Structure formats: C-alpha cells, structure tokens
Image (tube, rainbow, N blue to C red):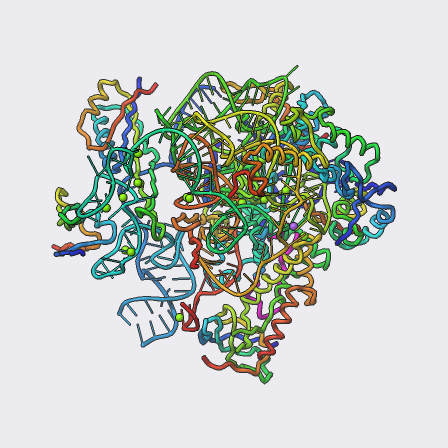
Amino acid sequence: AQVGLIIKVLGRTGSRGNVTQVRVRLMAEAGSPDYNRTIVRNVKGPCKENDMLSLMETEREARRL
Amino acid sequence: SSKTPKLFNKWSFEGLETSELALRDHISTTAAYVPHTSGRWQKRRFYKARMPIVERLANGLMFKGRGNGRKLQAARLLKHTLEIIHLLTDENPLQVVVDAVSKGAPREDSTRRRQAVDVSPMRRVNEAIYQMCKGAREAAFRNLKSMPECLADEIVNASKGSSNSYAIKKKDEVERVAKANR
Amino acid sequence: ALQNAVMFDKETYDKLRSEVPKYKLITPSIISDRLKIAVSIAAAGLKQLCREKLIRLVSCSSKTRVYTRIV
Amino acid sequence: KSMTFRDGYMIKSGTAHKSFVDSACRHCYMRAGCIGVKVKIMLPGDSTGRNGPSEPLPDVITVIEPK
Amino acid sequence: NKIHRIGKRKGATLKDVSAWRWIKTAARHFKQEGKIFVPNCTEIMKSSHGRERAPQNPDWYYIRCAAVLRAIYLRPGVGYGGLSKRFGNKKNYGSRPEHTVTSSTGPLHWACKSLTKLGLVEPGAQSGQRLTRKGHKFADSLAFQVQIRKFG
Amino acid sequence: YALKQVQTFGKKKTAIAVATVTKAAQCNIKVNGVPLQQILPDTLRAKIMEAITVVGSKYYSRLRIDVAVHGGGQVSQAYAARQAIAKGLIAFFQKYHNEVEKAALKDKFLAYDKFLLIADPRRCEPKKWGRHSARTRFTKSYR
Amino acid sequence: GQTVRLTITSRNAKAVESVTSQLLTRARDEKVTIHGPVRLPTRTLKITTRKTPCGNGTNTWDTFELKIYKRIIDLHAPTEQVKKITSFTMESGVDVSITILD
Amino acid sequence: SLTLIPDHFQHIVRLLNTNVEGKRKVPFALRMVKGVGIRFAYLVCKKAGIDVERRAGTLTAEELEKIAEIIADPAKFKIPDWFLNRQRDPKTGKTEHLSSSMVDTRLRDDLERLKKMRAHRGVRHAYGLRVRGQH
RNA sequence: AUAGGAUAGCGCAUUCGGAAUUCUUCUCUGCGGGAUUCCUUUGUAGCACAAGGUGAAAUUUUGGGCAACAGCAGGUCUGUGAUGCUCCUCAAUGUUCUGGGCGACACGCGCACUACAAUGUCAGUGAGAACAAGAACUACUUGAUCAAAAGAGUGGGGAAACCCCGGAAUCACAUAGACCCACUUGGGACCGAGGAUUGCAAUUAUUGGUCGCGCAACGAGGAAUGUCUCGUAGGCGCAGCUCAUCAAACUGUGCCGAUUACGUCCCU
Ligand SMILES: [Mg+2]
Ligand SMILES: [Mg+2]
Ligand SMILES: [Mg+2]
Ligand SMILES: [Mg+2]
Ligand SMILES: [Mg+2]
Ligand SMILES: [Mg+2]
Ligand SMILES: [Mg+2]
Ligand SMILES: [Mg+2]
Ligand SMILES: [Mg+2]
Ligand SMILES: [Mg+2]
Ligand SMILES: [Mg+2]
Ligand SMILES: [Mg+2]
Ligand SMILES: [Mg+2]
Ligand SMILES: [Mg+2]
Ligand SMILES: [Mg+2]
Ligand SMILES: [Mg+2]
Ligand SMILES: [Mg+2]
Ligand SMILES: [Mg+2]
Ligand code: NA
C-alpha cells in the first residue's frame, strides 16, 4: 500500500459529480524506481491539494474526463 | 501554575500520534478536559478535521430520536468506556482509540458499470467513527450487556484488526468487492 | 429463552467468592452471564465483595459500576 | 374584461410606494352589474410636505455642485 | 485529610454543602428524635396526582419535611402554591401529549404544620412562611456537621 | 484601603452573567452563591474551571469573585459564567497592573479558546407560517 | 414637597418625542426639578389572519402590528404651576395624564 | 439480598384459584390476581406485615392465608372506601371489593342488566360497538 | 460515612434579613455609529473570483415583508346594507320555538398523536427560560386539615408596579434506591363501579380525580414516498387563538443540540 501525495485537482468527473479526478505523485525512496513517478486516479470523498492517499495498486491510470 | 490538560483529569495527551501516515493531518490530538465545545465546526469545508477526536466520537452517539441532543449523556458514557478500555488493554485509552480510527474504514471503494476508486483521508476518518458507533448501538439493543461495554469491545477489537469488530468485517468486504471490479 | 436464577444457592455463592475476585474486569452484566443469575442479584453480590475489600471500585455512577481485582 | 390607461412614472414594489403613491377604488353600478374603477397618482413631492412627502426617492443620488 | 480547613476558612453555613447530604442528614435527625408529627394519610397516599405509584420509600415523609425546610431557608415568604411548583413533574396521559402538573398542596400543607409544631417555622408577616430564629440556627449547625463528615 | 473592585459581564444565547471581582484576604469564587466544587454535573464544572487552569491559579491569589447569572438554560449559564470570570481577570489587571502583564494573560486565553473573551453571536431563528419550524415545510401528498 | 407625574402615550413615535421635548423645555423655563424622562418598554399588538376570503389555495397568512410608546416625567411643583406648563396646544393622537404621587 | 434459596421455594404458588409466578417480587406477583393492581398490592403487603423486597415463592402457607383474607375483606383491615373497586352496588348498595373470578361474573351481570332494561348502552353492547362516544 | 474516589483557594473567615449614602456594569429606548470586497496574496486575463487579515459581524451580514407585463372560463353569489338576471313569499325557501342530525359503520385513502423498552420504566432530590394574556377577568396567601385526590371557602393585590426573585420540560445526581431481556414494573387501547365540576340543558358517555380491567395489537414495519445545509434537522415544553366547558390543530416563543455536502445535470 504505497502512499501518494495529491499535487493537482483536475475536476469533478461523475455524472452526479461525486467523484474527483486527481494527479498524485508517489512517495518513495530516492533510489527507488518509483521516485517522482506520477499517476492520474479517481477519488471518492472530499479532497484537495496536499492530501495523501493509500494506493492498493499503482499500475492503473484513470481515463481522463 | 499553568499545566497541560488531561481528559477527565486522568488520561494524558503527550506522545499521542497515529501510525497511519495518510491520516496524519486529519486526526487532531489537541489536549482538552472534557469532550464538549460549542464551536462552529461546520462553517467551512474542512474545518471539522481540527475538532478533537474524542468529541467527534461523542457526536456519533447522539443519533436516534432518543439520543438527539443528549451530549452530556454521551460524555458520561465515554467516561466509563475509557476506564473499561484501560482495564482490557493496560495501556493509554486515548492511544487505543486513535488506533481504531486509523484502521476502521476501507481504503478502496467501488462507485457508479461499477468502478474501483480510492478514498480521501477525510472520508476514512468519518467512516471509521460512523461504523464503530453503529456496531455498538445495534449490539446493545435488546441485550443484558450495557452500552459502555459494547462500545469498549468494538474499539478494542478494531484497534487490533480483529474480525470480531463490526467495522473490520465491513471494511474487508468493501475492499474485496472493489478489487473484484478493479 | 434465557434462564437466570433470582436467588443464590450454596454452590453459586461459593463460586462468586472465589472465582470472581481474580477477574481483570468485573461488571454486573459480565457476572450475570458467567454465573447464570439475574443482574439484580449479581449487582448485590458485587457490593458485598467491595465492602470486604476483596475487589476495588474503578468507575462509579448512579447506574454504572465497574470493579477490578486487587493487587 | 379589464382595461388600463397609463401615463408617466410609477413605482410598484418596496415600501416607499406607500408614501409616494395615493390610490383609491370604488364600486360603480350599471344596469347590467357592478363596475370597478381604480385611480393611482404618483405624487411630486414638496419640501413643505403639504403635497407629497419631503424626502426624495429612496434610490436617487444627487451630487452637490462645487462652488 | 479531606476535612481540613482551607486556609483561613472556618465554620460553614447552608449552600456550602451538598444539598442531598444535608437533606438526608436532617431527615435522619427527625426520625431518630421521634417528636415530629406524621399523619396517618401518608401510609396510603400518592405524593401527587401526577404520579402513578406510591413514594416507595418508607421514610419519604421525613425526607419531604427536610426538603421543604431547606426551601423556606432559601426563599422566605413562600407559600404552598410556590412549593408545589418545585415538586411537580410531567404526567403520562396515554395516547395524548404530556403536560406538566404542579404537586398536590395537601401534603405540603401537612409538612409546614409539622415543622411549625417543632418551632422551626412561623407564619411570616404578609403571607407565606419563614424560618424562626431557632430554625435558622438548626439549619447552619447541621451544615457544619455535614462538612466535617459527621452525619448520623 | 482602596476598594479595588471591578465588574464584568458575559453572554451566551439568552443567558447573562455578571461578575464582581474584589481584592480580599483569600481567594473565593462562587456562582449564584454556590462554591465551585459543589457544581454539578462534573462536565460543566470542568468548563468553568478552564478560566483558572489555563492561566494558572496564582493569578487568582487574593481575589473574591461572585457571579450572578440569569436566563438561558443549564448549559448556556455555564458558558456565560466562564466568560465573565475570564473577562473579569483581564479587566482587573487592566486597572491595577501594567500592560505587559495584562497582554501576556490575554494571549493565553485566546490561544486556547476564542469564546473565553468574545461572545458567540448565534441566536435561535424565528418561525414562519407554513412551516413547523424555522425551515421544515409541511408534508406534501399527491395521490 | 409634593410630586406630580406626567404620562405620555401614543401610537406615533414622532409625536411622542415632540410632546415630551416641549414639556422638558417649558419646565426648565420655570426652574423646576425634573426626574426623567423615562422611556418605558414599547408594547406591540399582533394579529395574524389568513389572507384569502373563503378557503382555497396555499394557506398564506399576513401579520398586522401596532406599537405603543410611553414616557413618564416627575415634577416637584404645585398643581397651579404644572397647569401652566401643560397649557399649550399638542399634536393629535397624544394623550397626557396627570397624577399626584404620595 | 444475598440470602440462600430455601428448601421450600416454589416456582408456581396457588392463590385464589390463580397461578402466580414465584420468581417476581411479592407486590408484583400479587397483581397477577384479577382485581388487584400495583397500587392495591402494595397496600395488601403493608397490612399483612410482609417485606416487599423478598421474592415470592418463599411465602409460607400461613402468609398466604393472611393475604387471602385481606383481599377478600379489605374494609376489615382499615382500608378506606374510596380505595375499593365497587363502592355502592346498584342492586345491593353495599361497598365491597371484587377479585378472582367474581370480577368476570359481576361484569356479565352488568351487561345483562342493561340489555334487559333496554338502555342505549345495553343495546350498543349487544351489537358489539363502542359505548363511550368513540367513532 | 455502612465501602467514601476524583475535583480551585492554603493587612482584613464566611453567610442572612433595618437605616443611610453614592453610582449606571447588567435592564428599559427615540435618534445615531458600525461592513465598504476595506487590506494582503493567487488564478488571472475592464467587470470580477479564491484563500487569508481586520473585526461583534466578511459577503444580497442573517431572517422576513413588498414585488412588473401577460393570463386561468382556478376559488368565493356560505363575509358584508357588494351586485345583474332568475326562484319562493302568510301552514312561506322569510322568521322564531321544541326535538333529531351534521359524530351512524364489516370498509378504503390523506395528515397527526402514542409506542414497540436498559442511551430504559418507576420512586426521590438539584439547578434552571422566553414570547404573551388578564374585569380595569387573571391571580397570591390562608382555611379546608384531629387525615386521599379533585374540590369548596376567606381576606388581599392587579398591566416593567399583582401574578413574579415568572421555581417549564428535555437535563443532572458517588440516590452507594427497585426492576434484569420478558409482550415483563414495556405499551395503554377497551371496559366496570363511586364522586366532584361547566352549563337553562351532559343520554350518544362535556371535562378532571380514585380503585379496578390490561390475556388489545405492537418486538422496528414490502413495493413505494416527504422535508431539510447551522443555533439548522431532530428532541422538549410554554403562551396566544378557538373558548360558559373541551387542543392529538394552527400562530408564536424559548431550552438541549448533531451527522453529511459545500457538488452535479444521471432523475424531476
Ligand atoms: Mg443493553
Ligand atoms: Mg426588492
Ligand atoms: Mg423537582
Ligand atoms: Mg412515555
Ligand atoms: Mg404516553
Ligand atoms: Mg410526546
Ligand atoms: Mg370554473
Ligand atoms: Mg346573486
Ligand atoms: Mg357572500
Ligand atoms: Mg365572516
Ligand atoms: Mg314557517
Ligand atoms: Mg332556505
Ligand atoms: Mg363535519
Ligand atoms: Mg433517559
Ligand atoms: Mg403487562
Ligand atoms: Mg407502564
Ligand atoms: Mg382547526
Ligand atoms: Mg437535469
Ligand atoms: Na415489547
């Protein structure tokens, strides 16, 4: 369960607008291959910039808009 | 002559921290004497994250038509609950409560086909409190065991990750369904 | 469905005075389930033990009583 | 049916219209039934206050001409 | 020691001690002395028509008399109607909404009469009831006993 | 000697509490004639006691405080009283001490709770016709 | 000596203040001792009724109000002198009462 | 009460042709008899000199005999007339208290009295309708 | 303390109810002041926005009232001495008086009230509101009381002056109180027998109070469906109006006091 930091909020994406799409940067060691790796994912619940997430899988990008 | 507050004049706040890094900024450990404060915590969007965690727990007990508005009663129930938790675990009750909140809610959820999504830190804290108070309320409905014992059992099991907890059972099922729709 | 005695017998009374004082957490509800007695008389039995300094009172309220074993 | 005949200024909403507007209504009886008549007048406004209120309209701003 | 003097404080008066501790201490003193007058009607009577069951405490009349004595100390000149507001409750009407009712003035009239016989209460000037000099002395003396944890 | 007396009020909902602070031989704080340790429940006693523990009991060494509070309810009066006590200490130091001492105390109160000195302005909303309360409309049925 | 009390009542706030001020100035011309004036609490009468004649449509109401203003002034003067003070024309809708305190 | 159970404890006690559960308090075990309520049961215990905190079923035969006598004739033991459930019988004019099966028997006679008289209340009872003005 | 925890104080100890001085912190209120995107930064491409600051209050300050032009065969001829046409008019469709009905019930539908219990019921004890009304009818105190209640009865006072220091209910209690998971001390429908009270008149029970019945369902409610974003929802009482007597209703008032969102155009 890696931890990612939200660095940009793209906008509400659901039809009812209850899901937000964000761009997160993976927090990893300096020598780790996941250094500064960035992903776009979908988030449920109130969130803003500088929040942190617990990614159960880090090999899946979300479809934009 | 000024001294740091202790909850119910018994439990110390120093050294209180959560081991879940993601929830580090959404669980407040500010010292207080009693879980009662007439603040405007719903004025702004994320302002409620700064309310002390024990008062958040107290607000979760005033739910049905019998309990709405009975905040002084909720404080009395919490006073006995912390004592029972201390006897069961032989450690600081505040630390045990913080642990239960840190791992009482799922991290992956499924929303409308159905898609698997992640959960923001604010919702993780909100859901853990909601589920634990819900499990104890139904366990004590028509039962010899009183409410403080039911609440103490739910919190101690949740802090250890045991499946006997109502919140833990619901957490595992939700995460399992989300991975199915991954 | 539950059957709870409303008065002590010889055997249950001895069980109260020997097994109970060694529990970590003592509560009338817990003792009632253990000894199969009504909560009303389990509460009265615990008061007698506390008077003789066999158990220690921890948290007290008009409707709640929590006890524990002595050192 | 109804008919209306207008000319000039007239304010209708708010509370100030009860001070600047003087109105009356009467019932008139023809040979075939009743007739309703109404009259409204927007008062000019006099400083003395005898004919209309002395205060100006609640949404008029006047700038004093400098010397 | 939990009964030591706090700095320069000495003595005690009413309102400096727990209300319940004073009331149950006075009630015991009345019963032990056995000079107060207890009417026979208290054996079979409800405290008020707003209650549904008997007072359930065999010493309820002694407690009630001690309670009204403390009330007169706090509010001199009070009458039976004023005391009924203090001892009222909310009544159950079945399938209809509840309302509050004042207590019956009968037992309150008896209680004041019993205290008057003991020489603790006198009919105050311009209506109402008030404490005698002896009654005022009795109340404060018992308060000091409660403070030093003496009791019965 | 000089009387050394100040007065101060505090408000909460419809509750109004008036506190009189006087220099005396020994510290003595009573509200409506009842000492602090005789106030129930213990939860409301702790809220009132915060006005002392926040700054420390040493600043109430030889002060006698009497608080009279009317209106409101069981909880409103407790909050009104604690504000009158806290504001009373500040007013006393403003009148019979210097500014550096007064400023230090005021910061400690504000860092803990803003409502120890500033009154909460919330009031109950009036009822309107066609509603059972301030905002609850009547039940609507179609069939 | 004796004290005389004047009470002023009306439903028009502007009228009450004008009458009260004139009494104050006239009294000070005669060099009398004045207590007051005191602004007594203002009372409002309320009546709410349904707007519609008959019964039909959404149940709507309107609220009618009517306020009453009251002032009192105390004078230390003989009854002959207070008659001189109050002997002036007044606005309509204002009534003044004279009583002698004990 | 911390008192050990006696050898003669009875789970069901026979009293006035009624089975009374012996596991409940004496005042609340007596109310299972028809014609005795919570208010009346406390008075019976007081007149019989029985502790109200002792459990039923521990009552002896002598105590049960005394209780039956008080219930049968409350007026003998100085119970006021306003406390009884039949204060002036319409057909007899005597104050008394009804209990056990006599409550049902007298109720049947009251209905038959009204019906034979052809009163409005009696007619409503015959057809099985409300009688106190309910709609 | 019967077994007594935790919780401030350690020049002049603290309480209660006659006479004097002084004085407006609290209360009363007619006219004023005060907040304006005012200050800083961001996204910025003039109009503006977001986050902070100042502050009692920071965005239409909060909540109301008023609200254009066109229409509906919407409602009201049961508000009026508002009305055209039409009907009855001396055993009258006018008007009085007596009685009955508008309340009847195997039934269906809308909106409420009380519950299904232990975050409880019962019995004590504590502290403690606001809007109002009153003949110029409401209400205090004392008898009744050498023995239920509800009543009767006597003096006295009254629109910031009496009621009134307005003793509301949620609530609190380390009360060392009773009950212990059961249709049970949950629930209180239905019904019996005394008695008092309003009224000229209580029968179809006008309304209170006492004992009894409680073996009437009801153990959380299918498909469906209503309202709501902060002193708000929910819970809790009080006043006014109707009113000789009767509030499960409406119009206001205060008390305790949250969860969630601060978004969208999927449904309407
Ligand atoms: Mg339970
Ligand atoms: Mg407008
Ligand atoms: Mg009371
Ligand atoms: Mg109830
Ligand atoms: Mg009820
Ligand atoms: Mg109710
Ligand atoms: Mg039509
Ligand atoms: Mg016509
Ligand atoms: Mg008409
Ligand atoms: Mg009309
Ligand atoms: Mg005729
Ligand atoms: Mg006709
Ligand atoms: Mg009808
Ligand atoms: Mg409760
Ligand atoms: Mg039952
Ligand atoms: Mg019941
Ligand atoms: Mg109606
Ligand atoms: Mg749409
Ligand atoms: Na049940």
Question: Compared with residue I88, is residue A36 higher up or lower down, i.e. above or below?
Answer: below
Residue H9 in the image: state x and y as whole percent: 84, 42
Answer with left or right where residue D18 lies relative to residue H79: left
Question: Is I136 placed left or right of C53 in the picture?
Answer: left
Q: Is residue E17 magenta?
A: no
Q: Is residue B6 magenta?
A: yes
Residue lying at the far bottom in this picture: please name it: A33
**Residue F79 at x, y = what percent?**
51, 45
Left or right side of F41 for I252: left
Please tell me whether the stretch drawn in magenta is mainly helix, strand or loop: loop
Residue drawn at 41 percent across, 51 percent down = F131
Residue at image point 60% right, 78% down: B180
Of B120 and I108, nearer the camera is I108
Location of residue I12 by image quarter: top right
- Using the rendered image of the protein, determine whether residue H3 is visible from the camera's viewpoint: yes
- Relative image position of residue I209 (x, y in whole percent): 58, 31
- B136 or H9: which is nearer to us? H9
Q: Quadrant of residue E37?
A: top right
Q: Is residue I39 above or below residue G18?
A: below
Residue I166 in percent (x, y) is at 48, 33
Q: Ligand 13: which quarter?
A: top left
Image quadrant for the N terminus of chain H? Answer: top right
Q: Nearer the viewer, residue B64 or B153?
A: B64
Work out whether residue F29 can be spotted.
no
Q: Over which residues does the magenta segment extend?
A: B5-27
